Length: 316
Ligand SMILES: N[C@@H](CCCC[NH3+])C(=O)O
Ligand SMILES: [Ar]
Ligand SMILES: [Ar]
Ligand SMILES: [Ar]
Ligand SMILES: [Ar]
Ligand SMILES: [Ar]
Ligand SMILES: [Ar]
Ligand SMILES: [Ar]
Ligand SMILES: [Ar]
Ligand SMILES: [Ar]
Ligand SMILES: [Ar]
Ligand SMILES: [Ar]
Ligand SMILES: [Ar]
Ligand SMILES: [Ar]
Ligand SMILES: [Ar]
Ligand SMILES: [Ar]
Ligand SMILES: [Ar]
Ligand SMILES: [Ar]
Ligand SMILES: [Ar]
Ligand SMILES: [Ar]
Ligand SMILES: [Ar]
Ligand SMILES: [Ca+2]
Ligand SMILES: [Ca+2]
Ligand SMILES: [Ca+2]
Ligand SMILES: [Ca+2]
Ligand SMILES: [Cl-]
Ligand SMILES: [Cl-]
Ligand SMILES: [Cl-]
Ligand SMILES: [Cl-]
Ligand SMILES: [Cl-]
Ligand SMILES: [Cl-]
Ligand SMILES: [Cl-]
Ligand SMILES: [Cl-]
Ligand SMILES: [Cl-]
Ligand SMILES: [Zn+2]
Image 1 (cartoon, helix red, strand yellow):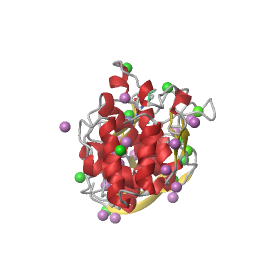
Image 2 (image 1 turned 120 degrees about the horizontal axis):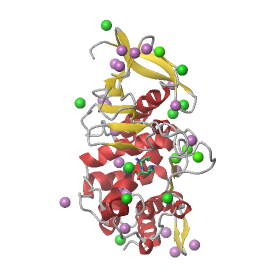
Image 3 (image 1 turned 180 degrees about the horizontal axis):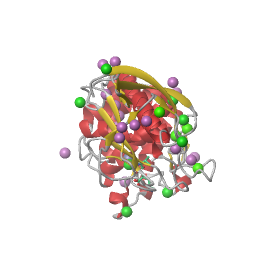
C-alpha cells in the first residue's frame, strides 16, 4: 500500500518482544519500507491460496497469539536482508532490492515452510512435530537463501546439485542465526522443532549422523526419495562447511578452522562467481578452492583448510 512508515511492537513465536517496521493507511500493515523495495508479510488464513492478504492490524500492536508467526516472518526477513546487505553487499535476493514477500498461517497443521519461486511460505506446524516455522531464524534465512540461490547459481533441485542447494540454505541460515546472535548453533530448526523434546533439531551441520544424514561422500544416498536425497546428502556439504569454519578431525583427516566470516566469504563467492545450475560436489570443491584462492592466495591457510575439509568428507 501507499502510506507512511510506522513502527509497531509485538511478540514472536518464542515469546520475545520486538519492534517491526509497518506502514499506516487506515490500518497498520506488515509492510517494511526501510529495506529495499520493501518487506511484505501476508496472512494465508489457514488456506493454501497465495500470497493471501497483506497483514493488516488496527492498532500497530501485535501481541495476539495469531500475530506471532507474522511478527517473526516479518522481523527475521528483515534480519536476513540486513545480513546479506551488510555482510555481502547484496541488496535483497536478486541483488537489486527485490521486495521480499512472506505468507504465514499456510494451510492447517502444516509441518513445513518453503520458498515457492516467488515468496516464502510458513506452516503453523501441528503443535507436536512443529510450532509455527517462522519462529526459527535459521528456517527464515534458509528459505530466503533459496531465493538467493535461484538468482545466482540456479542449482537444480535434484541429486548432487540439489544437495548443494540445500547445504547453501543451511549454511547461510546458520550464518544469519550467528549474525543475529540469539542462541546460535550449528543445528537447523531447533527453535521450532518438537516443542515436546529438548535439545533436538531437524539436521545437524556439526554432526549430520545425529539425524541419520551422511557425513562422507562414500555414505551418499543414491535412491529417488526426497528428490534424490537433497535434504540427506546436504549433510556431506554441511559437514565440510562446519569443518572449514570450526575445524576438527573427521575420519582421521584434520582441518584447521578459519572462522565463520571467512566461511561465509568463500561460499558466497563460490555461489555468485563459480557455481552453475548443474554443479556437482566435486565442482563445488573446485569453486570453493578457487574462491578461497581469489580471496587469500593459492598458498594460504584458507585454501588449505577448504581442501582439507573436502578431503575429510571424501569429495575429490
Ligand atoms: N524442510 C525439510 C524437512 C521438513 C520435513 C518434515 N515435515 C523438507 O522439506 O524435507
Ligand atoms: Ar505461535
Ligand atoms: Ar526490536
Ligand atoms: Ar522508510
Ligand atoms: Ar527488500
Ligand atoms: Ar539500499
Ligand atoms: Ar485481511
Ligand atoms: Ar482488515
Ligand atoms: Ar486488527
Ligand atoms: Ar486487521
Ligand atoms: Ar536477501
Ligand atoms: Ar555449499
Ligand atoms: Ar519447538
Ligand atoms: Ar551426494
Ligand atoms: Ar577422527
Ligand atoms: Ar590430516
Ligand atoms: Ar568465527
Ligand atoms: Ar557455495
Ligand atoms: Ar548465499
Ligand atoms: Ar547448467
Ligand atoms: Ar592445514
Ligand atoms: Ca493489534
Ligand atoms: Ca539456535
Ligand atoms: Ca540453528
Ligand atoms: Ca525440540
Ligand atoms: Cl496516510
Ligand atoms: Cl520471539
Ligand atoms: Cl490472543
Ligand atoms: Cl520488487
Ligand atoms: Cl527446503
Ligand atoms: Cl533476533
Ligand atoms: Cl533425519
Ligand atoms: Cl520422498
Ligand atoms: Cl583441490
Ligand atoms: Zn531448503
